[PDB]
Length: 313
Ligand SMILES: CNC(=O)c1ccncc1NC(=O)c1nc(C2CC2)ccc1Nc1cncnc1
Ligand SMILES: [Mg+2]
Ligand SMILES: [Zn+2]
Image (cartoon, rainbow, N blue to C red):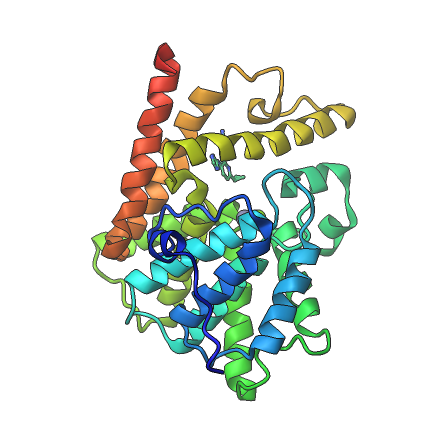
């Protein structure tokens, strides 16, 4: 109860910045995450005996994939933590509790394949969920772990606070289905231009949290160039594996995934930052001004990829 976590000075300072890397030491990530809950939400809002067990069950149910892994979970939670702490008043005590849990669980039991690959493979999970396949799987795994004994971190909420918090987490996890991002950004844009946006409209908050979630989920692109560059490798390791699996199914895959089209990557990154990342953070900064560091860091990296093409690295 009087048992706050501390961190090495460098981590204590660097953790409050959007562009924080959580480092190569697996065994501190749980301490980092707990620390984020305790500053973001209070020393009280989760019983330590129960949080720590939830964290360790969630670690266990991520897999050893190059990108969609436990380290990705915690990066995404960190980024959400930075947004909450720079947007201190805008969000309820419940939103704070649910969104960090949402982020930690957002990719539970991911195998490193797209919704598309399950559909073309005819994987059972595509039968049981037609759209946002992995995302309904991830929310489903999250509820399963919450029902293990000594794992209900929410035990002390009222029935209705409980239903609110699980409903936050579910929409939050679903929003990480980038297929849904595009229209969710379009609608939020139109509501901020035409000034109709209202953060007491619960359908409006929903969209906003949805964008926050896209932003956190993509936040490897808002890191210092050396981190972005090296995470790009991890994401492509998965893509090229999927491309290989597409070919096995006798389907020439999209070039993003053809490991014989490695040359076309830097142009592909350009396309992506232009089509997706820049738009995401632009609209996010438009809505939540204190998140600009994300847009600035995104732009730097876009520029770093322009320099790649021009032969300058
Ligand atoms: C939707 N279009 C495309 O996904 C795209 C197209 C052409 N090339 C690349 C593309 N996607 C990505 O690069 C990418 N995608 C994603 C999710 C799967 C969708 C997440 C992070 C990414 N980048 C990244 C991350 N961390 C460090 N460096 C880079
Ligand atoms: Mg995902
Ligand atoms: Zn993710």
